[PDB]
Amino acid sequence: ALVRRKGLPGKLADCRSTDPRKSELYVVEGDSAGGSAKSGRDSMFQAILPLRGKIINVEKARIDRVLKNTEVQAIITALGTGIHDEFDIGKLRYHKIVLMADADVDGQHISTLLLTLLFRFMRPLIENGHVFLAQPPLYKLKWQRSDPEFAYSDRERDGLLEAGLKAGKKINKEDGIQRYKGLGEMDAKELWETTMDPSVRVLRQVTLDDAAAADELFSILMGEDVDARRSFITRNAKDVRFLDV
Amino acid sequence: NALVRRKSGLPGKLADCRSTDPRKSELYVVEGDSAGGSAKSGRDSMFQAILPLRGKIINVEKARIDRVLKNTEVQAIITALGTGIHDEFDIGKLRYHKIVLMADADVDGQHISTLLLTLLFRFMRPLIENGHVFLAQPPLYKLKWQRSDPEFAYSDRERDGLLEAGLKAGKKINKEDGIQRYKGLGEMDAKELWETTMDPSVRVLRQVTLDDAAAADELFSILMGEDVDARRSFITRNAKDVRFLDV
Amino acid sequence: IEPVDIEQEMQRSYIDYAMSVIVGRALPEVRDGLKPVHRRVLYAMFDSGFRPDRSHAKSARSVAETMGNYHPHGDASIYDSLVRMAQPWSLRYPLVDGQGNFGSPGNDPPAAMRYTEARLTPLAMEMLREIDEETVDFIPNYDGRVQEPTVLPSRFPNLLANGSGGIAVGMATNIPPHNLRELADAVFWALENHDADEEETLAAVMGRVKGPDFPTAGLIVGSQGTADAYKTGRGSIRMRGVVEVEEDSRGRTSLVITELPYQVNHDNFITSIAEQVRDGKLAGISNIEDQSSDRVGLRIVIEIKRDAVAKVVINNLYKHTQLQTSFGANMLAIVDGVPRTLRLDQLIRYYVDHQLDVIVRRTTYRLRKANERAHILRGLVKALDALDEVIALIRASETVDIARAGLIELLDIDEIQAQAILDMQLRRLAALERQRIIDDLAKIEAEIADLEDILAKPERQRGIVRDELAEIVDRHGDDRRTRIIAI
Amino acid sequence: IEPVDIEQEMQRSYIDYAMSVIVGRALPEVRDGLKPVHRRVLYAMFDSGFRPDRSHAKSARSVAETMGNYHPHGDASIYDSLVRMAQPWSLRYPLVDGQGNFGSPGNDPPAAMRYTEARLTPLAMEMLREIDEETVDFIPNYDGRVQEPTVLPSRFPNLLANGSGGIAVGMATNIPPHNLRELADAVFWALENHDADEEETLAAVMGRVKGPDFPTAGLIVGSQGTADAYKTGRGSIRMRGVVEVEEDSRGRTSLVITELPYQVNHDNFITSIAEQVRDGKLAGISNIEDQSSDRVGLRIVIEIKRDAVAKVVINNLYKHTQLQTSFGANMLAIVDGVPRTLRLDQLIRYYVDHQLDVIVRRTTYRLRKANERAHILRGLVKALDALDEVIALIRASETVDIARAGLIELLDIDEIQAQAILDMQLRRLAALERQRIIDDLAKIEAEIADLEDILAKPERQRGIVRDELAEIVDRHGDDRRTRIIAI
DNA sequence: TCATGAATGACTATGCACGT
DNA sequence: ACGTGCATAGTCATTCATGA
Ligand SMILES: Cc1c(N2C[C@@H]3CCCN[C@@H]3C2)c(F)cc2c(=O)c(C(=O)O)cn(C3CC3)c12
Ligand SMILES: Cc1c(N2C[C@@H]3CCCN[C@@H]3C2)c(F)cc2c(=O)c(C(=O)O)cn(C3CC3)c12
Ligand SMILES: [Mg+2]
Ligand SMILES: [Mg+2]
Ligand SMILES: [Mg+2]
Ligand SMILES: [Mg+2]
């Protein structure tokens, strides 16, 4: 068991549960989204750490400079574990570390920067399945009489729309389908019922298979060598759609 | 008497002049970062310095002295003027013999003027007595004639006059672009500020004079003091006749 | 260089500041209960079409529209004002429908302008109802390019409903919010008893307006302060939150606070208790835990020691925290461009006066327009009766000016009417189409007679205000939130 | 809970980022030389009517319109983008007419959004010329509410004219600005010699485009770098400011810098010299004074010591300051959704291809509309020829449908034409108006013939681009600013 | 290490009146 | 001394590639 704040980051909205095994840390993109998350969360088991701006690339940046970064300090301090050789999973203050970023591209970028921080400084968190990715909604179908439905893809939107219309439900062609362009546009209720309510949230657990293969990929994509990254993109971007086929 | 100007122990916001002679030097105390920025560009950097003031100035009549001296904007003014305050005031160390207060023509500019004048009258009164304090009158309108040079107006009356005269003279204006109305110094560019408030050959300055010091003292204490009732009754009494002070 | 005396300058400048702040910034107009920024935001959104019959527009567009046309000030503070009008814990009856993160009753600030969308609420649509029918005076904006409303129609008593708080110069206002249904009853009585004096009117209105109705619910303790506010324009109203004592399996007791008085910050409230316990000022308290959520609302659990009495700790909380706090009522509003402290009967009466003004002006506008339509229709009917001649005339005319001038002489018609004949489509020459023109004339003349009848009868005018308001209250009226108890 | 491998996540997410940044953020489209934000800001202002034919709108309205409809990002950075497009020292040919404080070439920042107004410039109006005539593909915006243009008509070669600098992922662009008149000559040649191969075209275009023309004037030293850039797509162009040595009546000599190379901060430049003096790095310098003003422009006076040679100090300035600095050209632009480094001949050709596409599409649109109006006019003429019959028919109809159906039967007419006859006003039955309908038909049929001729002849199409561009250059073209000298 | 330029806003301080 | 609400924005740190 570990004490919660009521010596940790000022931005941290800690949980109430004294058990890390039961606790969860939502690492959120932006103050707005973090603000709403703080309200919609279950304050018992869920803590919120909003991250502001693009996270520093620990692959590129010198070690001392990374440690001066306010956002990195917040993460390291909140997780409780050390870094590199001084890492101690026993001090992990949350056994669930949910990264929650916008569905947009800059959210994807922030995810890679955070995953880079974790893989380089605190790898065991990934190896032991403590790192997760929340999948935000993209659409909210607002039926005239029925309860609203959330969609996490264009296909699901089309499906739920088709099903509802077939079922005799109806939507306004004005209000209609609200499209989320980021977490910051959501209120507390919406975030709870889509990304934080454990009975409906869509989390993806980050697994680490080949450590050596992961290592080189991180170094290529996140490293200082531009040529390697340039050629890698021109080589593999052509086939990014077909990774899961 | 000469004093060094900053060039790469004075306020960071201060855009000092080049002339080392206070007798020829001028300090433009400007409302806002935007206006101060344009002033810094449109000024004559030889004789004119710019000190932008951000936000409403602290009321030295209400706040205790220790709190006033901690205020960044007051410190900037006191430090820039070079003179001390109260008993340690020494006019010989005055870095500018012209202290031009330049605020928006709007209502909040008038408020800032009274706050600045309150600072000066209470901390550095001799600056007012010796006529080192001035008030810049910003333009309100810019008449953009189609073919002729543009004209600036500092009142509604003057706008009407210049409009009538120009039209009578055969000049013409677009009814779209037409007469640009200034709602503040921040809306002006460098050139506009120069040609209306900073160029000494066209600027409209008002020199603050101090006649009855005792009467000034009581007015300052009423308007700016902690006593609300006194201020309330004064306003309800005299606001009715503000238009007719100069009739 | 012109000389100016410091006394003249100081007096002139400060009075100019004080007066505009008083009349045109910090204090509400008695008729619609709005400050200039509120009025300008709402009208900007209205004119932009940001209405409940359409999806939320990005709030930046509302701020920008308000800035560019009506309110010559900063975008930031304008956004703050728009945000507050959308917060259910700030306004008893929100005028802005906000979509996104608009903050919380605690220290959680609202999201930035970029992240939020906003539109007018249905009630705000009643504030602006028929504003385009010359129901209110319009004046040129800050640069004269466009017109803005001096006051809104305000088809429900918004000043009393939503209240108002403002710091001016030499004075300040602090009007609490009220229950719309109770206000309506007061208005209904004022309309029926239009001849009642101030003494009677105050007695009646005070009976129906039982007291302020805060959006944060809570409690009102006592009746004197409420009475003082309504009779004097000033009164101190004691507010309380709601506390419910809970027992535990062990047998430990805990206090559960689910409501707080108006304008009490939840986080500051929790922090205040926390600081008052570590110092040693609220003994008997064992633990403070905020079990609040978006689903259960406010829920502050105060576990107390075994050697502690629940009410003793509660009374200590009332004493040393804002669990019990007073609302300093000061019924100050602008009346005809003058700041005035008003009795409750004066507030109701002035609003009712405004409504009657709105209805009479609306009727006048509709009557004028009705006559114009009738005027043109009469012209068309004359053309139809001599249609063979009219067409032959237009055809034989070398120009349209010749045709128009001829039509005037042919049928003894105005130029406006003659122009309408020319503007007539070949569609309207069909049999059934000729008939609609006739019937439309008959239709309008009935409408004109009705409108004339309304203007001639103060009874109908009052009836319209009553019925139209009654319709609004039936639709948008809600239950009381703040409970009123005795000492 | 679904499992995902870190390599899968990392690769997909980062590639998605690199690609969006490359194609849809940091790098310009080759056809109009615009990034998405630029295109969206300009079109927002255009659609809002913020054009040179009206007074400057508050810039907040442009930001809000861009933000709310097209660009789903923050208000701050959008304002920065709008501001930059209004700075004469940033853009060689500004696309935004700014009113107020938009900053300076030094560290003086632009005024906040609240203080500034903005509208499109006449040249930006050429970027958007006839965009409403289906000259470019439109797509749904970020929420499908409205349509936005994929590319602008760009009736002058904006990419080369204004240049572009952008940092993407895995690559970056740095295209310098050029003199519009020189670019036009290159385009004129490309149009005349439309069959010329790449070798000839590159030789021709390089002869006419003598080199970059920066808004900050200055000097270009040498010709190798310019040649490399045009032939390779990569090149290092040596820039210099302008220095004028002045001699005092009986004092020391001083260097007067009146121009600086592209994108050199004036304040940083002065600071760099000042800091390199006290550190004993630029001896011979006695005093540094900034005599710059809004009226004389840049004027940095560097008084040098008496035992110092002017030319020595200037070379020292070239060496240790940005008085001499290189422009790292990298001619990278998006072509058909793909990032590509281009030769100068490729940049011109791709632009000419775009212009021809625009003109052909415009002609097609106008031809379709011309046919539609002609189609209706043919109907009107039939009605006029049998005018007596037309009226009698409409009269006897119970509805307008019976009247229309009859008109089809009477004159052998479409439903569209008959409807147009029905919508016809009695206005047009006057003599001159009947004649006007006849002549209008004759005019359109003549215009249709012209339009058909254009589509069938590539010669005319190229001619249109030439003549229309020539008109633009004559009006908006200016002298060269950057002087080109030899080693 | 710095500049470039579109991307990812909270914090900071006064006026003003009034009540705890 | 703190809250209230309408008024009077610059500063702060990263990604990313390239050349000094
Ligand atoms: C200056 C300013 C603030 N501070 C006051 C001090 C002035 C001197 C040194 N800088 C600090 C910064 C502030 F804390 C908030 C705002 C606003 O909220 C705001 C707004 O628009 O809401 C506008 N300004 C500036 C115009 C005055 C603000
Ligand atoms: C967060 C942010 C900044 N901060 C992020 C950093 C980490 C935490 C401590 N604050 C520093 C500075 C900043 F310096 C500038 C901007 C902007 O200029 C800006 C803009 O819109 O231009 C937007 N943001 C926020 C969305 C991320 C900015
Ligand atoms: Mg986002
Ligand atoms: Mg102002
Ligand atoms: Mg503010
Ligand atoms: Mg920024």
Image (tube, coloured by chain):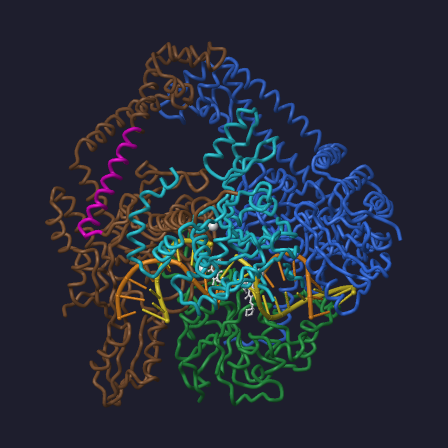
Chain colours: A green, B cyan, C brown, D blue, E orange, F yellow
Q: Nearer the viewer, residue D89 or D167?
A: D89
Q: Is residue D385 above or below residue D336?
A: above
Quadrant assignment, res C149: top left
Within the magenta stretch, is there residue C478? no
Q: Bounds of the magenta span?
A: C342-368
| Image coordinates for residue C88, horizontal then vertical, percent | 33, 61
- The answer, for residue A161, to whether it is visible in the render is no
Left or right: where C355 falls relative to C223: right
Q: Nearer the viewer, residue D103 or D381?
A: D103
Q: Residue at x 18, y 65 (%)?
A: C484
Quadrant assignment, res A57: bottom right
Secondary structure predominantly adopted by residues drawn in magenta: helix
Q: Nearer the viewer, residue C16 or A59?
A: C16
Left or right: where A150 falls relative to F3: right
Q: Is residue A202 above or below residue C42?
A: below
Within the magenta stretch, is there residue C344? yes
Left or right: where C51 falls relative to D309: left
| Image coordinates for residue C80, horizontal then vertical, percent | 41, 58
| Image coordinates for residue C38, horizontal then vertical, percent | 37, 51
Q: Residue at x 13, y 56 (%)?
A: C207
Q: Nearer the viewer, residue C109 or A102?
A: C109
- The answer, for residue D421, to whether it is visible in the render is yes
Q: Is residue D155 above or below residue A116?
A: above
Q: Residue at x 64, y 26 (%)?
A: D447
| Image coordinates for residue C328, horizontal then vertical, percent | 25, 62
In the picture as drawn, the residue positioned furthest to the right comes out as D487
Q: Residue at x 57, y 57 (%)?
A: D77
So how many labels did they put on this image?
Answer: 0
Left or right: where D348 falls relative to B232: right
